[PDB]
Image (spheres, rainbow, N blue to C red):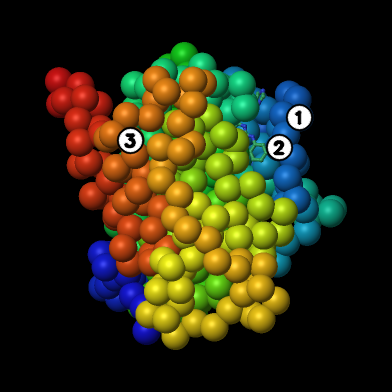
């Protein structure tokens, strides 16, 4: 029986309407208020375009969704409305649908993002600390509001490097946290899936996002994208095991009375824990200081209950300069 160590009763104390997303009644806006300027991306759930609000002539992002269940879309809408306004949380501006096809589109604030594949390689040591701190603000905020993002990864972190503005987007996999609830483990992107998802521990919590953040962080300071490069869910756990070691995995499994599938246990085998510094090289040396390793280490723990909370992470000395700078 696992439960969050913080913000566990957020949804218990709030009005039921706050988390009963299925009770939501979507208020559709005017589809003609937004015009497509150009396609900028795509996903398995939608096609994304840069658009313009014809009223104020301001830029926006139009997410045209592929067929989606009513329950599914209400969850994303409710979460966005509940979090709108919070620190670095992308803003949902409008919700519209095509009368004939019934195809819905979500209108979001526009961020002049730079592809992380091109951006990250140019980030200085300080930039990394700064942006990670900014992302942390978003995570502590949503967690404090009883919400798990469940899909933290570079693709879901828009960054306007010129303005140094960051936004956590794509809350389509986000869910409300309720003590004891068993969630679907089929969330997050493979390279950022926490051990709990990989071993089928369903009663996970906000801490899942902290593992994902840890993966992202490791990728940045060690300049290895992604850090844990697994081919499938089974291989993903193996890649993790080969770094953190199997002893820790075994202890984790025994603590939560979890039994790996025979095939998986075979693939994982036995591995010694590899020190973080073994991943240091001339390409990343200017980024792998003791404070960074200490911070990463406290994020990447098998036991989700062991990981730093977003609030704790923000106070880690690794971010002391960012904090001092902010307190000015
Ligand atoms: N919300 C939000 C959100 C806010 N900005 N934003 C941007 N801004 C950059 C637009 C751009 C202009 N030239 C290249 N890209 N892109 C995507 N893209 C996206 C793509 C696939 C899946 C999800 C998001 N999503 C978003």
How many badges with numbers are in the image? 3
Task: Find out whether the residues at labels 3 and 1 contact each other: C-beta distance under 8 Å.
Answer: no
The residue tagged 3 is 292
Q: Nearer the viewer, residue 106 or 213?
A: 213
Of the pair 20 and 121, the residue shown nearer to us: 121
Q: Please, is residue 54 above or below residue 64 in the view? A: above
Res 291 seen here: yes
Pointer 2: what residue? 48
**Residue at the extreme top:** 162
Separation of residues labelled 3 and 1 (CA atoms): 37 Å
Q: What's the residue at 55%, 42% (across, down)? A: 227
Q: Residue at x 27, y 72 (%)?
A: 9
Query: Marks 3 and 2: which is nearer the front?
Result: 3
The disc, 3 or 2, on the residue closer to the chain's N-terminal end is 2
The answer as to whether callout 1 falls within 8 Å of ligand 1 is: no
* Residue beneath the point at 73% across and 24% down: 37
Residue designated by label 1: 39
Q: For the C terminus, which image quadrant?
A: top left
Q: Quadrant of residue 197?
A: bottom right
Q: CA distance from mark 3 to mark 2?
A: 35 Å
Q: Horizontal and vertical percent for residue 201?
A: 50, 76
* Farthest right residue in view: 100
């Amino acid at each position: 029986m696992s439960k969050a160590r913080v913000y566990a009763d957020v949804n218990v104390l709030r009005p039921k309407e706050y988390w009963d997303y299925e009770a939501l009644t979507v208020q559709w806006g005017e589809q003609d208020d937004y015009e497509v300027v150009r396609k900028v991306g795509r996903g398995k759930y939608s096609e994304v375009f840069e658009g313009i609000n014809v009223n104020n002539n301001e830029k926006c992002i139009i997410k045209i969704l592929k067929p989606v269940k009513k329950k599914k879309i209400k969850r994303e809408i409710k979460i966005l409305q509940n979090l709108c306004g919070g620190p670095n949380i992308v803003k949902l501006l409008d919700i519209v649908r095509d009368q004939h096809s019934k195809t819905p589109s979500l209108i979001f604030e526009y961020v002049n993002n730079t592809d992380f594949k091109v951006l990250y390689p140019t980030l200085t040591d300080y930039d990394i600390r700064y942006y990670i701190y900014e992302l942390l603000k978003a995570l502590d905020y949503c967690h404090s509001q009883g919400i798990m993002h469940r899909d933290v990864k570079p693709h879901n972190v828009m960054i306007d490097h010129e303005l140094r503005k960051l936004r956590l987007i794509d809350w389509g996999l986000a869910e409300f946290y309720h003590p004891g609830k068993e969630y679907n483990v089929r969330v997050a992107s493979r390279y950022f899936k926490g051990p709990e998802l990989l071993v089928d521990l369903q009663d996970y919590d906000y801490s899942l996002d902290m593992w994902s953040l840890g993966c992202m962080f490791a990728g940045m300071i060690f300049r290895k994208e992604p850090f844990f490069y697994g081919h499938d869910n089974h291989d993903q756990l193996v890649k993790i095991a080969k770094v953190l070691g199997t002893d820790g995995l075994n202890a984790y499994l025994n603590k939560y009375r979890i039994e790996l599938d025979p095939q998986l246990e075979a693939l994982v085998g036995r591995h010694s824990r590899k020190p973080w510094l073994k991943f240091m090289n001339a390409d990343n040396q200017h980024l792998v200081s003791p404070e960074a390793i200490d911070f990463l280490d406290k994020l990447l723990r098998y036991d989700h209950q062991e990981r730093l909370t977003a609030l704790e992470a923000m106070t880690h000395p690794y971010f002391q300069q960012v904090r001092a700078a902010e307190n000015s």
